[PDB]
Image: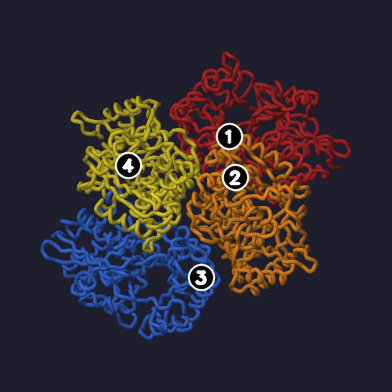
Chain colours: A blue, B yellow, C orange, D red
Amino acid sequence: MKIVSLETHIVAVPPPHVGGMYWIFVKLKTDDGIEGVGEIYSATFGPKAMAPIIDDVFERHLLNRDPHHVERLFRQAYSSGFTQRPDLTMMGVVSGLEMACWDIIGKAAAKPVYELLGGRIHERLRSYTYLYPKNAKGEYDYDDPDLAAECAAENVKLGFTAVKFDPAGPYTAYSGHQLSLEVLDRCELFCRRVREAVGSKADLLFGTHGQMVPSSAIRLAKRLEKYDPLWFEEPVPPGQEEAIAQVAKHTSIPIATGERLTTKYEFHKLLQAGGASILQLNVARVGGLLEAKKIATLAEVHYAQIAPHLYNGPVGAAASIQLATCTPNFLIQESIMTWGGFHAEVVKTPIRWEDGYIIPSNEPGLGIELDMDVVKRHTPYTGERLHLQMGEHPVDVKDLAPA
Amino acid sequence: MKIVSLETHIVAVPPPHVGGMYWIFVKLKTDDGIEGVGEIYSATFGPKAMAPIIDDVFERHLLNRDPHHVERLFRQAYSSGFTQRPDLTMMGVVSGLEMACWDIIGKAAAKPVYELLGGRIHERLRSYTYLYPKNAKGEYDYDDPDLAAECAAENVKLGFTAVKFDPAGPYTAYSGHQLSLEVLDRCELFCRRVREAVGSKADLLFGTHGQMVPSSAIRLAKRLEKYDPLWFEEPVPPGQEEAIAQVAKHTSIPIATGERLTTKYEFHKLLQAGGASILQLNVARVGGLLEAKKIATLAEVHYAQIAPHLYNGPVGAAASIQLATCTPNFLIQESIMTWGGFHAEVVKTPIRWEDGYIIPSNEPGLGIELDMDVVKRHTPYTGERLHLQMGEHPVDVKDLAPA
Amino acid sequence: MKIVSLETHIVAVPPPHVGGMYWIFVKLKTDDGIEGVGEIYSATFGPKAMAPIIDDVFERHLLNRDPHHVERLFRQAYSSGFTQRPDLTMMGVVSGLEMACWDIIGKAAAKPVYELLGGRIHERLRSYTYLYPKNAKGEYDYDDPDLAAECAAENVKLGFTAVKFDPAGPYTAYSGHQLSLEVLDRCELFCRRVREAVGSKADLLFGTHGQMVPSSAIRLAKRLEKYDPLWFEEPVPPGQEEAIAQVAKHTSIPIATGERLTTKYEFHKLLQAGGASILQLNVARVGGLLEAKKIATLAEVHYAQIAPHLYNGPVGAAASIQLATCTPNFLIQESIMTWGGFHAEVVKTPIRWEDGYIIPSNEPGLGIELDMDVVKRHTPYTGERLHLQMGEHPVDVKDLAPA
Amino acid sequence: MKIVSLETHIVAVPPPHVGGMYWIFVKLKTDDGIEGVGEIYSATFGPKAMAPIIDDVFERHLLNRDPHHVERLFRQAYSSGFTQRPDLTMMGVVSGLEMACWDIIGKAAAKPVYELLGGRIHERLRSYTYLYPKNAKGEYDYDDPDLAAECAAENVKLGFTAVKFDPAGPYTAYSGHQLSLEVLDRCELFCRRVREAVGSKADLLFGTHGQMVPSSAIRLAKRLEKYDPLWFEEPVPPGQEEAIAQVAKHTSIPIATGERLTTKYEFHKLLQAGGASILQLNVARVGGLLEAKKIATLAEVHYAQIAPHLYNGPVGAAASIQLATCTPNFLIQESIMTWGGFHAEVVKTPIRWEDGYIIPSNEPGLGIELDMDVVKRHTPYTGERLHLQMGEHPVDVKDLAPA
């Protein structure tokens, strides 16, 4: 059995772009006709560059190889061009290729991938969502704490047991910075209002984006402690484990991070420093499902938990669900609302969500398949923006703009 | 003043490919007609992918910006797509763009870049080269210690005060590994024969490529100590600072590393661990000249030295020379032989080398300019290989193949 | 191009001596007629000793040298007389000479210095001032918390977003000491009253002067936490990094320090210890603009910020502004009120301040020039005192005198 | 009793300048006619600047004060101008003033100072000297190992039990650097030849001057171990305690340092790091005799020893002898040959040296007094040089010049 072909499909997400501007899918086919699908999470470079990058990685490191050989695939990609340290875009690309290989492995075995990576532990998966409150004009409003609270209350009625929000203002190319008193006040007020709305029915997830230097993150944490959030996410920019550990040392709120980290080597450094107790790996960035399993293993020996990140399509979500289902130290899975809308439209069988939980597929492989007619209608992406972007200018202390 | 255009020129290096398979050059032009040139060191992905990557970075982060704004450029590139941790390919790309900006800054000021980044310290720069011994058929031979010794002796006659060689066998996608006794013996024999040939006239640079796990590197170091090498290069794969520090703790031979690291953040982690005392940054990978100056600064406070890496074209070499000239903790500059051959042919005014030293240009900017007629004749690159590659299969203990 | 002459001008600051007793300026001229100006921050010895010191340093280490060679200048001064560790007065002197060299470098290039040291990042610079409340007799009163609060409120009306005050009593030759309960109470009361007056419109900067031993600083910090100051400045005397780090470990208030430290080597020791997260370098003490840039670089890799100190003339302020403008991890710039009064009178073009921010000059060099007619009228200084002094006697526990 | 007057005498040392270019003496007189003498060790600035510096410190911090109040004197000087961290020149100045105060204290009590600072422990003091070999032209020659060996043998005949030499080449403004193989070979050869000449009758003191970066110092130490030197002096430049500790960790040769450090605070940092086991304080630099006693105390609790430095006049030597005589952890005292020549001529009663040992005075105070007729004949100093200087240019690897 060997991989003989690749198709790349970069789908434009319709406005208002829930889950980002575009999703990068890859489809692999074997010599005996088994198809696998994967998703790539990487936006250092735009989709016009990503297409030839993916072709290059595939041709050099996967074409004509056995899909079962996922260690080989990872090592070849990781080492490409005399590197053998993490290249963030390469790791995103190989994540997509590798999970598509797992899709094929599972289909060949007639088993869900979770039955091959340790076996089912969970019958259903606790989930959370970002709050998506709308103002009177129908635009998402991330500035109004009362709209956030109302939205949280509605999510609790749906069955959610945790909600996430980021009231901490813009994250910019010059972050970390020192949040103003008005922004600190707003962060506290969001927690107060959301807590009032949900009581003990839902945890608060303080979903920051690395806006802060550690001294500012610590000031913020002291204010948030009275509302007992389940976590304080990405308190400082990634890439400096001692700095994030400094925040953890100075607050009782659990630190969660990881959506911008890749490979077991980076998570090892983070855990060695005491930098976080909740790891938010994205399976479409870290190196694929086996590498994600390895990261979960590191977490186990530190008594840390995994809470996989998701701000992308349903294929990466499906892979994330496969990992979560067989992970003993699983905390919660990020969901994009309840997986309806375009997340459901772009696949043949949507991800199942009920009363706060994701219900894993029992189908072989990743339990996901693109609807190619829908995919074709939403390609190509012609937008100017990357999947996500950081603010271009430093934050001004007098500015009250949302994240 | 602003940058209004970019040209990318990926030049095929003629056989036998000294300095690699291809060199990636960028040319910037300003609105008032000043031209700057730079070089990118990145081979995670091949040149077919690199061309649209470079266009993407330029369009998003540099087009219509002031070339003086190199902090801005670095921060925008470093943060691209909500990353803000090192993306190895992006850092290579921005290095080329940034050094081209410095070329323009220097031309506008009518000064060499070294007169703006701290001022001249060195009248000339100590240099070294890899040994390039040829067998009877005219092929480079990295297996014969006596040919290496003869070559070292000839380099000493030219005036070189240091020579580099790697007798430690293949570096592969599965490195680190544990060197066999026969390979350990060969490493020792190369040092013995080269030392006999050069006496105290030249330092030995043991130019390993991360072949080893730390326990193997330590076994090797104990054997090499009797020959007093100036350094033991990349004893283990990059990306794990505690592992390389373990080697440093167990040998008196200075550890040199850095050609596969990028940004001040990675070098900080390395130095904090005690991982190396000689930093082999490549100015075309680390983030550009200002970022390289920042790395040199980190080295200063640790009483470490810089020894910039060079396995690429004369534009990156020119930038490296600019940094070295104004660096107080400069040890030595890697040279590709004496900068003749294609390194001289592809530029209007070749890099000057005399009696073991590089003589820095007194011309404004980087002191380098491509000969576009030569460039045009050596584009496009149509080769199958990346600039450098790692071995595809794990080393077999019975194998005696060269690195 | 070379420096051929020096003039030293030690200007007496008129009563009530805002910014200290005297400012030490140096003027350099090149062989082709370019003039540069700098300022020296050093008061170990009085101005009668400083004049021949400056002549000595200039003659030995700068006369007939190229102003571009600022690495050379720093290394020669730093090493003078077989020292090569920080000599505090020498570092102040070389800071002035070096920034005057940058003034010349910028003028020769027709660029602001910030366009050569990384390029503009900030269009304007957040600033703060000490509170200068007056009693009914027109004397500055640092004892009355209500006068301080009223003054803070007026500063907020001007547009300031931070204010500084030191209610912690005398700093003496025998500091650190243990603050009395009455002084601790007063410190808390100042914060309470000032916070009431400014609300969330301005940060509190607790501007202590190293009065305390660490155990006392910790007692004070616990009292101040409820008012969420942006920083706790110089909680203990300089020169002992473990002691200041002990304070940082025991409070959530950011520790700021550095106005009495010099060179990257001292700031490295401070950061390695975790001693502070906000660095208050004075560009006229630390070794000059390049050395200050190096210190800012150290801060970057620790995710620390810079907040340059200023208690001196507008030339040092101009240099500080040049650094801040091109610094990505810039927090805030100390201002002496709004740069009016004698700070404006002594220069041809005053520093521009609007609505809480400093607006950097677009002029070449440091963007500053002394008005020599004003300088001549305010020389010589004939005062008995040093620029600043410490109390001669130990603090008595029953004493309630102001700092 | 109070100090009412100061005289400063900066004496030109006749060629060939053994003990440096000039010695800085201070003479204090009390209101009831007791005279004290001291020496200042500081050459950051030249003697033309030192004279008004000394006047300034004296006027502000000692004039009209009781000479017994040496804690007060130190604290006032240390704190001068809102500093309260070490200012190297100020510490040299106060050292001279303070030891002159001790001279007065001892005279008033009719006791040697050593009888007041702990009491006699040693009847005589083990001493060493630098080797001062002369070539055929009568010039001191520091390049010839056989001349050094011959000189060592003659010193052993005089009774010396230790000899010092520095074969490690120039120390420059850009040190540390990486010693060449030829220099490493020469260092080893000096040790070999000197050891052959002295056998076990004298220890070797490897008297380096901070030429090296730590990686180079470690390479050198491995070569020197076979000759069992008593110490490896100043292996790296001062001011970085972790770097010097790295050398200590990697060699069995004791590390000695301290002649360029000042105050108990700096020696504390050094000892905390494990940076040295032999402290070479100079009593005329560290802050005076009480501060030196405090440094010796720090050494005691670390089981370190003191070996005071001396490269200056007989007044500082006399003070050093006073400290040594009452120090339980005393190793050896640096002597300038046998204290003859100008060291004897400039005082009324020369320092006594017999069979390898200094014999402490039994006279009150420091047991030393300047011959003012000789002093007058050798003032003023009109030389261009500082007391000691560092090389202006970086060392070239091909250069074989002496230190």
Q: Position of residue C354 (x, y in %)?
A: 59, 65
Q: CA distance from mark 2 to mark 3?
A: 38 Å
Q: Residue at x 33, y 55 (%)?
A: A86
> Which is nearer the eye, D320 or A289?
A289
Give the chain letter at badge 2.
Answer: C
> Which amino acid lies under the numbered mark 4 shown in the image of this protein?
Leu
Say whether residue C367 is left or right of residue D35. Answer: left
Q: Is residue B377 above or below residue B82?
A: above
Q: CA distance from mark 4 to mark 3?
A: 47 Å
Q: Amino acid at mark 2?
A: Gly
Position of D308 compared to C364: left or right?
Answer: right
Q: CA distance from mark 4 to mark 1?
A: 36 Å
The local secondary structure at tag 1 comes to loop
- Under mark 1, the amino acid is Asn
- Which residue corresponds to mark 3? A399
Q: Determine the residue positioned at 69% across, 22% down.
A: D14
Q: Is residue A34 above or below residue A194?
A: above
- According to the image, label 2 marks what residue? C36
Q: Which mark is residue C64?
A: 1
Mark 3 nearby-residue class (10 Å; few <14, some 14–19, many ≥20): few
- Is C61 left, or right, of A107 in this rendering? right
- Chain letter of the residue beneath label 3 in the structure image: A
- Amino acid of disc 3: Asp
Quarter occupied by the N terminus of chain C: top right
Labelled disc at residue A59 = none
Q: Quadrant of residue D103?
A: top right
Q: Quadrant of the C terminus of chain C?
A: bottom right
Camera-nearest residue between A90 and C188: A90
